Image (cartoon, rainbow, N blue to C red; front, side, top):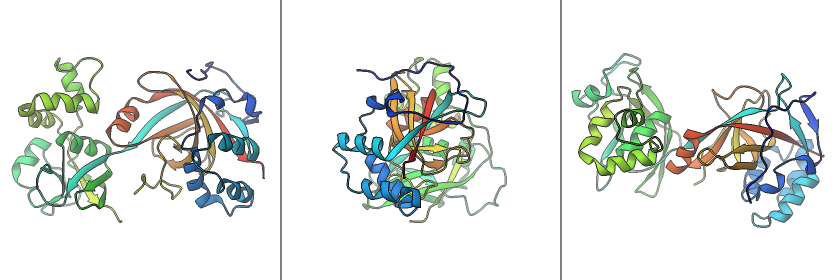
Length: 331
């Protein structure tokens, strides 16, 4: 029932080594559910390249339910190449990312009681502000509200990420991105709850912190004030996941960010790794559709877990050994 496991520390004599599909350990462990969705987004940018025209034409005939036919397609139109680091090692690091998804309103009302703030107009770009607790008390933020959300813990973790999306009670969606900082030190509230015994070793996830906050509503404001850092936001230019560097919406658990000088955008990658909390095998066909400032090296990926806080808790814990095969179209 559980998938193929990595034998660590193996090495290879070439950067790319063609292998048979029968030599990809883990290929049969992937259901392939969702892979055709990310494949069609890939083809939106690749279909007219000479090497991709035939594969993309065939790909448009596949539905997303018949994973038997999708498996036959990948085995027929692509060859897998075992991918090594330039030092010959096959092991590399898989981390994770997500897109925060909050629920808010453009006006303060009902459950929407916690503001996200733009950079305060009464202030000069890049001048140091006080800690969060005094910034919130000075009055300097009043009238600089960008939108009002559902939950102060979600707002806090949106600040940690710097960017995300707010589903508004409109029926519209607002994308927010990085709008500046008070340049004061970050201090994790999860570590605070652990260091002071309020949360057990297991449990300082975003969900465990939300639960503790639910239990201790009159302590929440003081907990958040233990982090002096404060992040501001800007509204981004106006259905599916975020758009990545390839220019297409990312697909949860089927898109990775890569170092594009090692793995060009558009490359499908068979990823063998493990799940962050249970450590079970995770064997997944993904597509290189994004990049990131921390994602540098050869066998290196950021796995896109999807939208919302369960995806973020998986992303937060992901720091797993991994193996890669790059697919190239037979063409």
